[PDB]
Length: 225
Length: 231
Ligand SMILES: Nc1ncnc2c1ncn2[C@@H]1O[C@H](CSCC[C@H](N)C(=O)O)[C@@H](O)[C@H]1O
Ligand SMILES: Nc1ncnc2c1ncn2[C@@H]1O[C@H](CSCC[C@H](N)C(=O)O)[C@@H](O)[C@H]1O
Image (cartoon, rainbow over all chains, first blue to last red; front, side, top):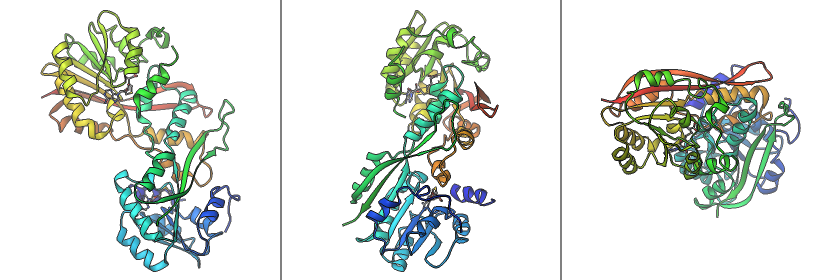
C-alpha cells in the first residue's frame, strides 16, 4: 500500500551494469536451486534484478504486491520472463501460481524486512506452496547491523548536537532478521536450511576518512520435506 | 534497540564529563524555555530515559530537585557518577507502573521530561508508559516529551544517496533497512489526547550537526515535542 506509492514515484524516471555485481550470490543459486525448475522472484519490484536473473534461468516470473511495480516490470517481459501481481500474504494466489508454473524455486531480495513481521507466517506458507518438495528459496535480507552502520556514519560525518547521540539512536530502528533469526524463522516453520552465509556491499563513494560505507546483508537457501 | 548493550559499550570508556565540556547550555537543551514557560516551577523533575546522566546534569543546574531514571542498569551505574544533593538516578522501566507508583510515593507529584523514550520502546508498551506518566505527574504535574520525527529516515536516505550510495541494484532493498519512526507532530498529539491528556504546548524543533558534509550542507536531525497535562 505504501509500496504502491514508492513504485509510482520511482517509475517517473538490453544492457547490464557488470557481471555478478547485480547478483553476487548467483553461483550459490545455481549450486543449490535446480535450473530445470521455473524461478519466482517474490518482491520483484521494477524487474531490474529479475531481468538479470533471467540471463541464467530460462523460465522466470517476477511478482510483487504493487501494480505500479509490475506494470513498469512488464516493460521487460519476453518469452521466459513474465510479471504478475501477488501479495505473499495471499496463500490462495500462491496456490494459483503454483498450479500454473509448476513447483518452482523462489528468490526474495529484501522482502521479509519489507513487510510487517506478523505477515511472515503467510509469506512463508506462500513460499512453501510455490516450492512443493523439489523447489528451493534463496532469501537475502539487509541485517540490523545496517542501522549500526548508519549510527557509526552519523557519528563522525554528521554528529548530532552534544549529548544527543542516544536520541539519534532511538530513531535508528534496526531490521528484525540477522543470520540466526533468519535461520530460526525458516526452521521454526519446518524448512531445512541447505546453505546460509553473510555478504557485504561497499559503496563506490569515498567518505572523508578514506572509509567506504558497507551495506550488510545475510542470505539462506531452504527446502521442504 | 537493546539498551543495556548500548550503555555498557558507551559507558565502557570514561570521571564523567561535566556539561560545560560539551556546550555552553543552549545547544544541549534548546527547548528549556518551553519547559520553564509551561511546566510548574515548584515540582521535582523526572528525566525518563536519563541514560548516562549528561542532559539530566544540565537540567539539575536549573531545577532544584531532579531524578533521572532509565531501563538500563549500566546507564544508571554511569549516571550515579554525576550524583550530588538534588540530582538522583534510579533504574525505572516506563512499562513497570508499580515502580512508577513507588517513585510517585517517594518523590511526590512531578513534571517528567522524555527524550526519545517513546520511539526507544515498542508501540505495544505505549499505553503502559502513558500510565507510568499519569502516575508520576498526578494532578499538578506535566510532561515534556521530545521525539525524533519519522522524517529522520528520509534525512538518512538523502545522506546515504549522496555520500554512501548503495551498490547498483540495492536502492529498494536498502529502503526496507530504514524501519521508520511512527510519532510525527499529529501522531504524538493524538497518543496523549486519546489517553486523557490536555496538550498545552506542541511545536517542531530542528537540531543541527556542527560537522559540515562535503556537499557544504549540514545534517538536520528533525524533532517534535509537546507539553501535556492530566485533564
Ligand atoms: N506482501 C508482499 N508481497 C509481495 N511483495 C511485497 C510484499 N511486501 C512488499 N513487497 C515488495 O517487496 C519489495 C521490497 S524491495 C524490492 C526488492 C527487489 N527484488 C529488488 O531488489 O529490487 C518491493 O518491491 C515491495 O513492493
Ligand atoms: N521502557 C523504558 N523505560 C525507561 N527507559 C527506557 C525504556 N526504553 C528505553 N529507555 C531509555 O530511553 C532512552 C532513549 S534514548 C536516550 C535519551 C537520553 N535522555 C539521553 O540524552 O541520553 C535510553 O536511555 C534508554 O535506555
